[PDB]
Image: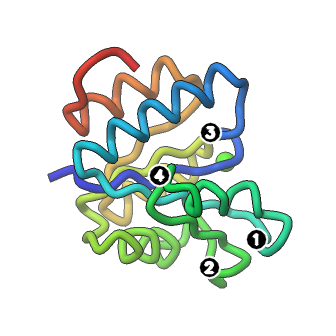
Amino acid sequence: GMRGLIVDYAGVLDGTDEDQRRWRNLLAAAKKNGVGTVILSNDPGGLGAAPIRELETNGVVDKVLLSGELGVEKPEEAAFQAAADAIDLPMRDCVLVDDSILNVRGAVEAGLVGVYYQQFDRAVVEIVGLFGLEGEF
Ligand SMILES: [Ca+2]
């Protein structure tokens, strides 16, 4: 089943305080349902990405992967594969949420389920449905 949630950081998790609260609640619900969570970001990484990495350190997500550290970037299949590997799942069991249509299409082509993030209200319906989460997020 849909066991893995792979999300971008910039343009997805770094919005308004309201949007970030909504994402924190959604990720917490996903975690409680056993969903593995990875941030897969095209970002140079290193010290400058400490805000992103803190989300792994503090347990908000299971793992943070940054292209500048991986040596591969979205939409390359290898980037998605690394994310899936990080939470011990096949790519086919993962959902990618990303604000780049090219990244979402790349994911779908690799066998993931894709969700295009343009506004939280639209994307949340898809996410909640895919993972069978209960309540309004
Ligand atoms: Ca992005």
**Mark 1, residue position:** 45
Report the Cα–Cα distance between label 4 and label 3.
17 Å
Beta carbon of the mark 4 residue lies under 8 A of ligand 1: no
Real-space Cα separation, disc 3 to disc 2, in angstroms: 20 Å
Q: Classify residue 43 as left or right of residue 65.
A: right
Nearer to us in this view, 43 or 92: 43
In this figure, which residue is indicated by the disc labeled 3?
12
Mark earlier in primary sequence (3, 1): 3
Residue at position x 64%, y 49% in the image: 9
- In the image, residue 127 sits, relative to residue 40, either above or below, namely above
In the rendering, at what x and y percent does residue 30 appear?
33, 42
**Separation of marks 3 and 1 at Cα, in angstroms:** 17 Å
Question: Mark 3: which secondary structure?
Answer: loop
Closer-to-camera residue (76/67): 67
Label 4 to label 2, Cα distance in Å?
17 Å
Relative placement, left or right, of 66 versus 105 is: right
Circle 4: residue type: Arg
Foreground disc of the pair 3, 2: 3
Task: Indicate the secondary structure of the residue bearing disc 4.
Answer: helix
Circle number at residue 5: none
Amino acid at circle 2: Val
**Disc 2 from disc 1: Cα separation:** 12 Å
Regarding mark 2 in the picture, which secondary structure is present there?
loop
Which residue is the extreme one toward the bottom?
Answer: 71
Query: Dividing the picture into quarters, in which one does residue 111 lie?
Result: bottom left
Distance between mark 1 and mark 4 Cα atoms = 24 Å
Relative side of 119 to 85, left or right:
right
Q: Residues within 10 Å of mark 1 (few under 14, many from 20)?
A: some
Q: Which mark is residue 105?
A: 4
Of tags 4 and 2, which is closer to the observer? 2
Label 2 belongs to which residue? 72
